[PDB]
Image 1: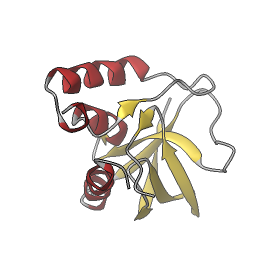
Image 2: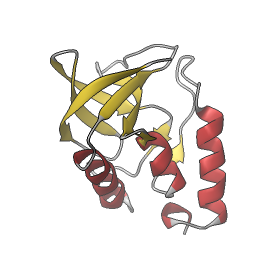
Image 3: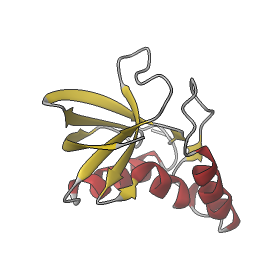
Image 4: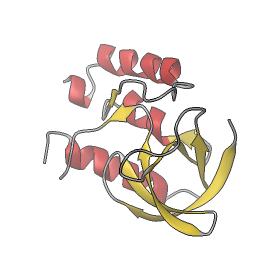
Length: 130
């Protein structure tokens, strides 16, 4: 898997963000995470603000596709997003603002990493695990 540059256009929700990738606007859905929905579930606005702040304040945004299918049925890209080297998917789970989702079409390179982060957020009874 390799990282590619992208530019933030607009954060839409805790699990979805619009990015300029290879010159064209595109909607990305964060791989392996399930965040409370804003469109409004409990912690939804917290998750949304977290994702937004983390990406708006970064110097560099990179996208990393996994080895499985790259887009869902709605046309959104399926990827791990990094903000200044830190993976947003992982930060959300670690902070207890998302649960790890079921592996989708072979996209599970970081499932264990995220699983570990979630167990810890759980032990700490953070946010969602409150």
